[PDB]
Image: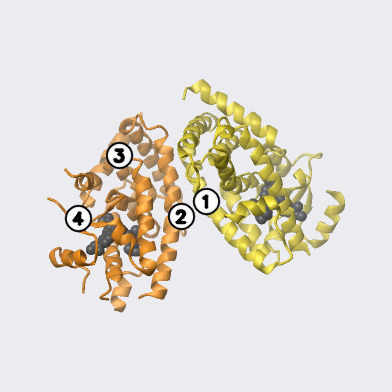
Chain colours: A yellow, B orange
């Protein structure tokens, strides 16, 4: 509630976020813009360059399986970040699981934007860069499955948030009291109110020329709710066709109840 | 510096909101709570008496559930016109590209109807006919085949939304923010719609602080409710689709086309 206490919370969440996530937005921006000789990624834009890149760093399943592996690693990183949110580990254990169950996808998408520009996405911890054209041009259902992630990222990235903002935003998402099945909504909201207070002040101080960025950033939490919906309705269709494909037990369990 | 300008905008939207809308939330609350007693519809027989007393302009299907459905349609058509006239009083709206005016209303009316319908609802039923009637939630929820499940989500939303305890002066600004959404599909000139929405957001923010000083982060919680609004309108149109395909004058068809 007091200003020094809110800045204190912001520093705690940023320092923790740096510790939980291996590749920040600031390092990703440095790789994506370039002018550097040491951080230059190998670019995959077609089938042949994908074969060479595996020596350096079916095709559509192999790329899909690559996304699965990272999303599982991301859920692990998000779970570790979540534990550091003051108050989270003190909630009813069922609500802990329930907040994570519905929060990871909205967060995975948000942080996936940090790795993208309009032309592609960083992979292999930034050693690689796979183009948007190549992904969107994958066959049958997989092409249309990759592109909405880019469509979201382009719009989210125009807000020009940095990592210090995202650490607080990611926390507000996790601590949503409107998830289905929560047992005690009140203590989750009390945490979110503080986190929101912390976000508002962080955004006011860090982005003082950006009018009403707080309101605009909460409205992006709208776009995320719908985009996760589309994602799970498209993934369900894809498993019905690709009898081979299987999902990591961690992702499996999140999607069992959607 | 701009604070008085924002209170002026809040008063401008409040005075207009009273003129545009037949039954305010403050008048509806007095009816539902007790402080001219309305006619109560709880079942089939009392519905026939209510239409035989109150002149339901919409009655020419002999079935009960279709006749209630058709009553909601007729009132929604009136609300679209009420919202359309209120929109003209939002500073800057009439100066927009006529196509953008049409587009903002086309995509906004549903979220607004849902929002203001909450003003007429409590956990036990809904006001109709300018407050002269009161139709119970049990009766509506228990209508047959798809009609029961179509009525109830509106109550489930209203109960949660009304927990914020907004009054008409708050709602006048909130409604305006919705209309002026710069992300509607097909807008030709987004900038001045966002420029107006930024003003409206500032005015809502200060209004909510002055009017609700004990309610922490109510501004945030109110924006988070526009999440609930996009999703429930999505389900709503997918439910109308099932009702048009399973159930059923071309002129009447044409009036209700949207
Ligand atoms: C051989 N190819 C690769 O190694 C590779 C190719 C392209 C992209 C990537 C990185 O992909 C992500 C990274 C991160 C991260 O580094 O934090 C986070 C997310 C993705 C990513 N999830 N996702 C999904 O579909 C997905 C999502 Cl959103 C959420 C939950 C579950 C899944 C999935 F299980 F079903 F995959 C993507 C779709 C398209 C794109 Cl472009 C990226 C992703 C590696
Ligand atoms: C003779 N009157 C009746 O028979 C009757 C029976 C029950 C309720 C009502 C009032 O109904 C509304 C009033 C107002 C208002 O006074 O401001 C505003 C909205 C409704 C109302 N729209 N809606 C819809 O379905 C709907 C919605 Cl949400 C949005 C857009 C379009 C539609 C529709 F076009 F498709 F109808 C309802 C569903 C359930 C309930 Cl309980 C109320 C409503 C009158």
Q: CA distance from mark 2 to mark 3?
A: 29 Å
- Please provide percent x and percent y for residue A180: 50, 48
The lab-note entry on whether marks 3 and 1 share a chain reads no
Tell which tag, 2 or 3, sits nearer the viewer.
2
Q: Are marks 4 and 1 in contact (CB under 8 Å)?
A: no
* Quadrant in the rendering for residue B9: top left
Q: Are marks 1 and 2 in contact (CB under 8 Å)?
A: yes
Q: Are marks 3 and 1 in contact (CB under 8 Å)?
A: no
Residue A121 seen in the current view: no
Mark seen at residue A176: none
Mark seen at residue B9: 3
Q: Are marks 2 and 4 in contact (CB under 8 Å)?
A: no
- Please provide percent x and percent y for residue A92: 54, 37
Q: Nearer the viewer, residue B122 or A233?
A: B122
List the residue tagged with mark 2.
B231
Q: Nearer the viewer, residue A223 or A212?
A: A223
Q: Residue at x 41, y 61 (%)?
A: B236
User: Is B26 displayed left or right of A240 in the figure?
Assistant: left
Callout 3: residue from which chain?
A: B
Mark seen at residue B130: 4
- Sequence-earlier tag: 2 or 4: 4
Q: CA distance from mark 1 to mark 2?
A: 8 Å
């Amino acid at each position: 509630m007091e200003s020094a206490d809110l800045r204190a919370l912001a520093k705690h969440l940023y320092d923790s976020y740096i510790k939980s996530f291996p590749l920040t937005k600031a390092k990703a921006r440095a790789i994506l813009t370039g002018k550097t000789t040491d951080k230059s990624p190998f670019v995959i834009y077609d089938m042949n360059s994908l074969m060479m890149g595996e020596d350096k760093i079916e095709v559509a399943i192999r790329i899909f399986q690559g996304c699965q592996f990272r999303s599982v690693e991301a859920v692990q990183e998000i779970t570790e970040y979540a534990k550091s949110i003051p108050g989270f580990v003190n909630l009813d254990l069922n609500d802990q699981v329930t907040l994570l169950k519905y929060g990871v996808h909205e967060i995975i998408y948000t942080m996936l934007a940090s790795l993208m520009n309009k032309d592609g996405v960083l992979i292999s911890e930034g050693q690689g860069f796979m183009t948007r054209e190549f992904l969107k041009s994958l066959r049958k259902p997989f092409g249309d499955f990759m592109e909405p992630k880019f469509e979201f990222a382009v719009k989210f990235n125009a807000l020009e948030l940095d990592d210090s903002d995202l650490a607080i935003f990611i926390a507000v998402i996790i601590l949503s009291g409107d998830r289905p099945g929560l047992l005690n909504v009140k203590p989750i909201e009390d945490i979110q109110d503080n986190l929101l207070q912390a976000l508002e002040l962080q955004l006011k101080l860090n982005h003082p020329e950006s009018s009403q960025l707080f309101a605009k950033l909460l409205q992006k939490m709208t776009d995320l709710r719908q985009i996760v919906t589309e994602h799970v309705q498209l993934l369900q269709v894809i498993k019905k066709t690709e009898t081979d494909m299987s999902l990591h037990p961690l992702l499996q369990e999140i999607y069992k109840d959607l």
